[PDB]
Image 1 (spheres, rainbow over the protein chains, first blue to last red):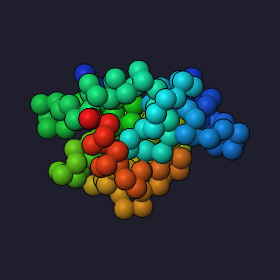
Image 2: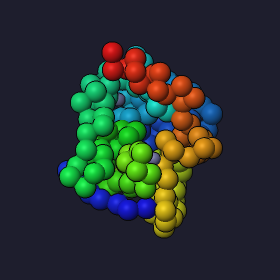
Image 3: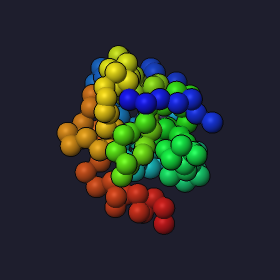
Image 4: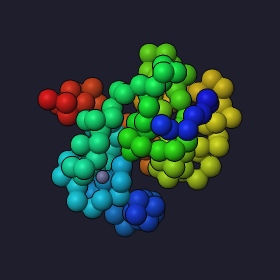
Length: 7
Length: 136
Ligand SMILES: [Zn+2]
Ligand SMILES: [Zn+2]
Ligand SMILES: [Zn+2]
């Protein structure tokens, strides 16, 4: 899964 | 704290409907609209404000379950674009589940997967209806 850090 | 309350759920010492699955508040006054479990009014307020908010990457801004999170997994389903934070996944699906999902490619999220139940995370059979009322 792609991940990102939340804004 | 959500951690200990979920512990109790797993231990069958407490019903998941009686805890806010989003923040761990015991002051449950309503049902989480997407997953089996309770919800407090604070988190409802958060949900109404954050749900279906999107970043410039074309994916949702905040964790579907808790409307927060710091690292989130993104659903590959273009009809969905939801995300789930590592903390809710490890807590409710179970320890290691986040790492397991991160290595999966492609990955479709818990609001897409036909099985609908992943550990303690159970998708409501009627979530569109629930949602619609949540909003009204
Ligand atoms: Zn709450
Ligand atoms: Zn979360
Ligand atoms: Zn999805």
